[PDB]
Image (cartoon, coloured by chain):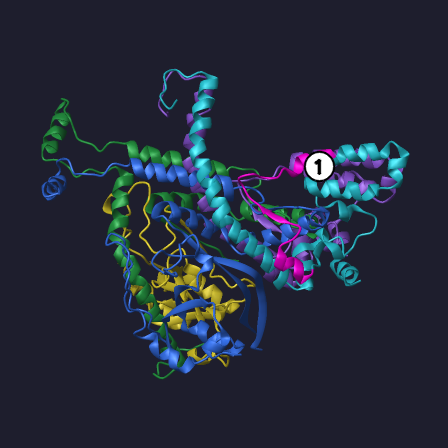
Chain colours: A blue, B green, C yellow, D cyan, E purple
Amino acid sequence: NKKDKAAIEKWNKGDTDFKSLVMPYSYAQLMTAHAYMVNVFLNRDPIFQTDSLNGDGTERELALESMLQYQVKAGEMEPSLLVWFMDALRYGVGVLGDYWEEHVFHQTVFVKKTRVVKGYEGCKTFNVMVYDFIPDPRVALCKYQEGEFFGRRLDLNVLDLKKGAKFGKYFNVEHAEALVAASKEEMYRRDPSIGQQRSLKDSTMTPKGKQVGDISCVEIFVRLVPKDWGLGD
Amino acid sequence: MEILYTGASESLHSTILKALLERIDLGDTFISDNYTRWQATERYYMMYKIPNKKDKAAIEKWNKGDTDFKSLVMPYSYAQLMTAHAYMVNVFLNRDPIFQTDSLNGDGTERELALESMLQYQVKAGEMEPSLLVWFMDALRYGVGVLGDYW
Amino acid sequence: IPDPRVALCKYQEGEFFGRRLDLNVLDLKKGAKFGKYFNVEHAEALVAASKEEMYRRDPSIGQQRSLKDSTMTPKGKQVGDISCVEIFVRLVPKDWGLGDSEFPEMWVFTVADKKYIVAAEPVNTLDDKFPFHILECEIDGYMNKSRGLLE
Amino acid sequence: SSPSSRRSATEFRGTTSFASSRLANLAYFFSVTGFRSLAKSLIVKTQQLYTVEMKVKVAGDNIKGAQSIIVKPEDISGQFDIMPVDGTLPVDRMAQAQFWMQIMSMVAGNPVLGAEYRLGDIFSYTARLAGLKGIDKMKIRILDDDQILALILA
Amino acid sequence: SSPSSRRSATEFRGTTSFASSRLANLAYFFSVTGFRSLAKSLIVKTQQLYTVEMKVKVAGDNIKGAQSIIVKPEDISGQFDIMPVDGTLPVDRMAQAQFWMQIMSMVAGNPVLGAEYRLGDIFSYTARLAGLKGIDKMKIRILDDDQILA
């Protein structure tokens, strides 16, 4: 409000006055709801449990459950599952993702040998912001599984692209590292009150050569007839 | 490894240093943005009020023997932070074992009792708890709390 | 010092993380014998001249100033603290000049007064994570400025 | 009953029983629509993607034989034999264990019943379900991970 | 209602159950996000960095054999077999001890059950879990630290 700047001035001088505010109520209700959901689903001891239709199932339930906990516990799924719930309540829709990860890393040990160590292999999960999902607009969001395509907007670190190329996951790499510099044009942004615009973006030089930064990318899954798309018969 | 300061340029020391510095500088940008805000919370913790003009007079009266009103900032908010910090300390730190282990399979059960003992030696004899209380206050007070670990 | 290009929640995904620290001269010296530190002669020189703290706590908090950092030993020499930074980075060795590999690895460096590098080493812990742990009051999962109860 | 004027105990329980109801209905929607999807997906991958060796390492002594883990791809595709469950209607393993203990008592008596059931297994199973998870170790002969793989290999 | 006064045996149990709920949700966030990280890290180092000799010294009679302490590096990297737990959902060792005791009584009856289990060990284990921790010292033969290492 216009009257506010004056009040702030008074406060600086030592006096006191009224500055305006928006009442809390609604926030409190969202927060109370989020709690109900976290307690009902996430804070439980097993989280994912299995029930069996026939006798054969009973034999397999105990083991399956164990393998599922390794994955929630050792794959750090829960931090991301809390957000999915907030999002739905806050924005109206919440989108999550799933993938399989085999992780390997290298470490130098002293003379001066190198080693490849094997880490977690299992499913991992992630959250897609509201502004990042790309859906099929011709089927309902509820009916997403029926439509032709779904995809997400993502940022990929150059170092990762390069490592992947060795394994065989990626290709056309030379052309890609070129875009590190101007790749990020951010169209949909957060509210002005929220900060983190960033600077000297993604461009840290390295001692001998190259630069280390990210490239904007999109991942899409499509249902297709191979003959038509040229990818097979 | 050893990188030595020959002082000559085009040296491993010189080339590496430059790189590291760029990284430190990018990082420093974040702190700069959040600094003013973090400093305000401190005033709130300490319940400080910029002194009013009428106040100096009052202090003078008090010295002479009389009494008058000197202004203040109301407590409420402090009380709520303090009540919250307590909940957290009780839930996590004041417990008897603090770090406990659960096991997925049978093999784990064999190893749980010993591991736990080794973990207490470390919390108890390494004086971790004094530092874990602060991490919790910081988060509530400032919004973020960072902790570290070393052998 | 964080990486400003990934969210604070997602710190483990970014290239670097580090802290600003003060190291006592006596400790640097002891370490040099064990083999932990190097370039020591140059470092002791900065004892008298190394203090600038750009970001400081609010005046209300009561942080004070000794204003006289160093003390002289009977035989000559001064005991004091040299300001330093410790940073952990993920790097391709070939490029950084430290070896031959094309795969990213983690190393730690300590730089003193932004002029000399007093320590560097590979990191060899089975997990690949940087050694720091962070707690935040607010529940957004994307980049934001976190709030605290007082604010 | 949200209005409060000196509520007694039944009254107190009553408004809260009722207020929760609209929130529980949301949960139920969430559970069927999206939690279920995630859960089913995780189950498919764990069954198909993990190799047998990895399955012993993650699951251990819980794999009492071939049946416990091995599965044909037909089952994975048609989703047969097991169903995902969630927080909204949880399963109580403790109750199940108590019934099993009663069954075992009956099998002990009535020697004819005893002839056609394997009592030791009922004891092992009940204990594991209750949560003990170490009964196997206590047995005179203990199976190591390498030993289990060999058994699975059949 | 949080602030109703002259409350019954039920309000005392209703606003407070409710009020704590928003605080518990904070705890849960803290637990998953950062406490977990610390805990997992401590666990890795203790397993990898300590030498076996040191492990006997820190852990003592709790090491009943090779299985108890020795571990391959694969496990340390893949985090298999044990999971960290915290204050928010604690484990009750006392209850576990009681179930084990019932198990022990059943083993004693039904001599066939007795044949395939080691009863002494069940007794030692239950006692240690409950917190005794001196049971071993009272046995006729006592193992010293040097003996354990061997």
Question: Which of the chains bears the disc numbered 1?
Answer: D
Observer-nearest of A84 and A75: A84
Q: Residues within 10 Å of mark 1 (few under 14, many from 20)?
A: some
- The image shows residue E121, relative to residue C124, as above or below, that is above
Residue E109 seen anywhere in this rendered image of the structure: no
User: In which quadrant of the rendered view does residue B4 lie?
Assistant: bottom left
Magenta stretch holds residue D82: yes
**How many numbered badges does the structure rendering display?**
1
User: In which quadrant of the rendered view does residue C72 lie?
Assistant: bottom left
Residue E17 seen anywhere in this rendered image of the structure: yes
Residue D98, percent across and down?
71, 33
Left or right, residue B123 beside residue E105: left
Residue E14, percent across and down?
44, 25
Magenta stretch holds residue A115: no
Observer-nearest of C71 and D88: D88
Residue D128, percent across and down?
71, 43
What range is drawn magenta here? D72-99
Secondary structure of the residue carrying tag 1 is: helix
**Residue at position x 82%, y 32% from top?**
D106
Mark 1 belongs to which amino acid? Answer: Ala
**Residue at position x 89%, y 40% from top?**
D115
Report which residue position mark 1 lands on. Answer: D97
- The image shows residue C63, relative to residue C5, as above or below, that is above
Left or right, residue E71 beside residue E77: right
